[PDB]
Amino acid sequence: KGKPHCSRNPVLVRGIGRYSRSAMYSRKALYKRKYAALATVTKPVGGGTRVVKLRKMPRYYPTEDVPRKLLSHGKKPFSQHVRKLRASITPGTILIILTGRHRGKRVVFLKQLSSGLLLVTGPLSLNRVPLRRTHQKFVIATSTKIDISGVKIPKHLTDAYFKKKKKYEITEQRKVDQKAVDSQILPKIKAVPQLQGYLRSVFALTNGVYPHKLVF
Amino acid sequence: SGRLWCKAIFAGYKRGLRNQREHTALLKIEGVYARDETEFYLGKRCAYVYKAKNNTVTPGGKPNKTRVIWGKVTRAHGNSGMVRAKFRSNLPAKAIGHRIRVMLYPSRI
RNA sequence: CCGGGUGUUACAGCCCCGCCCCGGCAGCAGCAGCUCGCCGAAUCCCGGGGCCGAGGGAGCGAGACCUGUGUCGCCGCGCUCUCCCCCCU
RNA sequence: CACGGCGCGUCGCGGCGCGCGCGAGCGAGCGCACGGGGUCGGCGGCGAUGUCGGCUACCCACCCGACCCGUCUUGAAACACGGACCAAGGAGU
RNA sequence: CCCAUACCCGGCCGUCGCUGGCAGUCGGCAGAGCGAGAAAGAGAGUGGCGCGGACGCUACGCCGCGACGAGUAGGAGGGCCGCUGCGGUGAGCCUUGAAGCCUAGGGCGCGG
RNA sequence: CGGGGUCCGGUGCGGAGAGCCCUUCGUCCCGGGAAACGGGGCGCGGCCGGA
Ligand SMILES: [Mg+2]
Ligand SMILES: [Mg+2]
Ligand SMILES: [Mg+2]
Ligand SMILES: [Mg+2]
Ligand SMILES: [Mg+2]
Ligand SMILES: [Mg+2]
Ligand SMILES: [Mg+2]
Ligand SMILES: [Mg+2]
Ligand SMILES: [Mg+2]
Ligand SMILES: [Mg+2]
């Protein structure tokens, strides 16, 4: 019993607390918190009753087996890895896809997903790309942004939604979600002059220009 | 539609004067000629692309005559923008002074 | 405007020297991001690139009233077995 | 502030130090991790007569390296000597 | 700024040292330890349900830590390297094909 | 028309190679800006231009 209180010290730096041992002994008020000192089931049968033993022994042991592994601590499954995002990437930023089938297409970025992939879309009405996922490494984040803080995207879309199944047919749910997102995205980009044509165009490298020199 | 990589020339292997180490290549990336300009290309993937005689399978397409040796940029070399690269297999010596595409998708911007 | 000469503050300035609270005020090995140093128990934070991941039965608690489990030792922490208050969903 | 009980407190210098008892040296759970050497409870493609894999080994190309062995000798690639090539025999019993 | 077989970190092979560790596989007849700064007893005593638990150990074996590795003349050790014959042994192989010889085939061993 | 004179402009080369040109998602409607002289044509027949 007892409601779980939050930690009494803000994290000063990772692994170091703001308050020392005595300050903690005071804040926790420990000066007044002193304390001092299955495998069988009976069943009826039509005889009598039988004590059936669940978890019965195997009917085959292999010729030989591998031993156990030593224990390690710092290794966690991909589900609960901490997700990182580049500073230059914020909702409403223009990205340049570098490796997909949509090579060098300028695309608006909306949301960071749960597994770290970026939920991205440039309204397919003009640059022909749907709601999609893209790894944050394989995109160039240019320094041009629109304001999409006042748009709502459905909460039902997620990595489970975008996960591949199994010919691929687009679903009516996909169509309606794309329409719902673009109906709010498009007027925002149409406010900025010469932005729809910019998104329609495709990025490329000509001779005499070098990425380390040019800024974006 | 356009070109999404940068030109480099496979100048030669990392070497002394009488010894050469074929597990590391030297690339001259076009347009960069100093150390304070090569930090952009560190860690970028590079590809040596060449044609052959037999057809080979390709990702997302029908088989063709093209083959690729992949690699990555490891560190700067010298003071004049030369770059050290490491490939999954040591490049053939016939590629000296030929084109290697350094791409951008291992991006940090 | 220039050249030559005289000279001692004039229609420019320079150097030294008693004091005026070492006169006073910043500031200070200065992001006036190069005017000249040695450092850090008087030092910490964040980030990027490259190579590698060898080893494989570490035990925990259960108590002769039980026989489970495979997140374990050292180390650093947080919460509860006290009671209140504040804020956001 | 790696301070935290009550006492008998001289176990004591004037309280702090610092001793003797307090069922007598047994409070428990959960959780996070810069903690006695990596894991994913993360994914993507291409596959039947043209494609996948085969270090080495067959042939060829390229860059770097690279003088013919045995022997005597201070010193051998030597303008020092033995040696066209191959098979069998051949010398501390 | 460039690089040696030098130095630092890591993997692997071997040698040497610790004259290191393991007979404790002590199981419903049992209780799973002897890594823990401090020479020595998880000391013995007498009075006030479910029947269950991986591998091991050719001890000439297995396992763990460190350091090191040039070599002529020469010395020593190990060869499950090789050739021929003899005593044993393989209820061995073989005319449903031995020996020998050839091979752009598949492999093992640092090497023989 | 070319070569000289004066004069006027630039001169760390803005008539700059630290530069210039072309710039490619495509198609469909209507409007504005430029053009009506323009665009495209082994679609054309000639005339010059070159050692
Ligand atoms: Mg040579
Ligand atoms: Mg001789
Ligand atoms: Mg001699
Ligand atoms: Mg002679
Ligand atoms: Mg002679
Ligand atoms: Mg002769
Ligand atoms: Mg012979
Ligand atoms: Mg070492
Ligand atoms: Mg030796
Ligand atoms: Mg042959």
Image (tube, coloured by chain):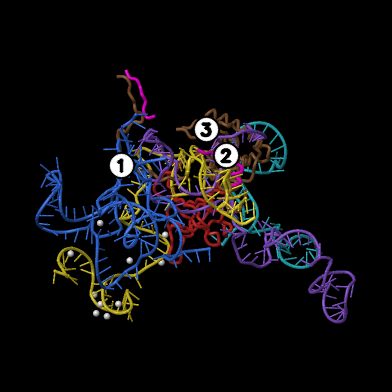
Chain colours: A brown, B red, C purple, D yellow, E blue, F cyan
Query: Is there one chain holding both mark 1 and mark 2?
Result: yes
Q: Is label 3's Cβ within 8 Å of ligand 8?
A: no
Quadrant of the drawing holding the N terminus of chain A: top right
Tell me if residue A209 can be seen. Answer: no
Q: Could you tell me which secondary element the residue under label 1 belongs to?
A: loop
Q: Could you tell me which secondary element the residue under label 3 belongs to?
A: helix
Q: In the rendered image, which residue does mark 1 sit on?
A: A64
Residue F16 position (above or below residue F45): below
Q: Which quarter of the rendered image does ligand 9 occupy?
A: bottom left
Q: Nearer the viewer, residue A109 or E34?
A: E34
The answer to which quarter of the image holds residue D65 is bottom left
Badge 2: few (under 14), some or many (20 or more) residues near its Cα, within 10 Å?
A: few
Q: Which residues are magenta?
A: A22-46
Q: Which mark is residue A33?
A: 2
Query: Is there one chain holding both mark 3 and mark 2?
Result: yes
Q: Which mark is residue A161?
A: 3
- Label 3 vs label 2, nearer the camera: 2
Question: What chain is tagged by disc 1?
Answer: A
What's the CA distance linking mark 3 and mark 2?
49 Å
Q: Could you tell me which secondary element the residue under label 2 belongs to?
A: loop
Q: Residue D20: image x %, image y %?
A: 51, 48
Task: Indicate the amino acid at tag 3.
Answer: Tyr
Residue B32 position (above or below residue C4): above
Does the stretch in magenta take in A33?
yes
Q: Mark 3 vs mark 1: which is more N-terminal?
A: 1
Q: Is label 2's Cβ within 8 Å of ligand 8?
A: no
- Label 1 vs label 2, nearer the camera: 2
Q: Residue C51: image x %, image y %?
A: 45, 53
